[PDB]
Image (tube, grey):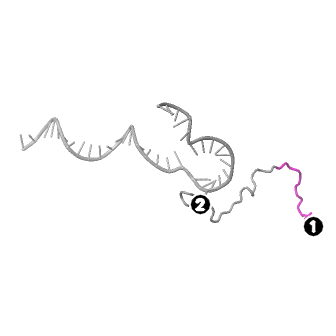
Amino acid sequence: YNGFTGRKITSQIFIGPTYYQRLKHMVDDKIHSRARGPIQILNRQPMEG
DNA sequence: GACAGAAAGCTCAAGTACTTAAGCCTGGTCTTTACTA
């Protein structure tokens, strides 16, 4: 049944329990932004990493 | 003066030196100086 309106769904959906894994990769460890931060010593260019 | 031989020359196959080798990103760990003097 549709969660929003309560109407039945015309197609019949395949459902069941399946074993799922959470992986090490998370967005909080990958999100990054830069604006006039640290400057490399030799090239006077933005840092790496 | 006509031939042949010995010449410098020239070109053409093998061998050698040198080059590049995807893009971005995240971590971790280790180490710069150990050894003779």
The local secondary structure at tag 2 comes to: loop
Residue annotated with mark 1? A7
Q: What x and y, as percent, mark residue B14?
A: 38, 38
User: x, y percentage for residue A44?
Assistant: 55, 60
Rendering coords of residue B26 (x, y %) = 68, 53
For label 1, the crowd category at 10 Å Cα-Cα, with few meaning under 14, some 14 to 19 and many 20 or more, is few
Q: Is residue B3 left or right of residue B36?
A: left
Q: Say which chain tag 2 marks.
A: A
Q: Nearer the viewer, residue A9 or A46?
A: A46
Instruction: Inspect the image, locate mark 1, and give the three-letter code of the amino acid beneath it.
Output: Arg
Q: Which residue is rendered at x = 76% and y = 50% of the image?
A: A24
Residue that numbered label 2 is attached to? A39
Q: Position of residue A25 (x, y in %)?
A: 74, 53
Q: Quadrant of residue B12?
A: top left
Q: Chain of mark 1?
A: A
| Farthest residue, direction bottom | A5
Q: Quadrant of the N terminus of chain A?
A: bottom right
Of helix, strand and loop, which mostly describes the magenta segment?
loop
Q: Tell me, yes or no, whether the highlighted magenta stretch contains residue A9.
A: yes
Q: Are marks 2 and 1 in contact (CB under 8 Å)?
A: no
Report the disc number at residue A46. none
Work out whether residue B23 or residue B29 is closer to the camera in this orientation and state it: B29
Magenta region, residue range: A1-20
Quadrant housing residue A2: bottom right
Which sits in the foreground, A43 or A7?
A43
Badge 2 density bin: few <14, some 14–19, many ≥20, Cα 10 Å: few
The disc labelled 2 sits on which kind of residue? Ile
Horizontal arrangement in the rendering, residue B18 relative to residue B29 (left or right):
left
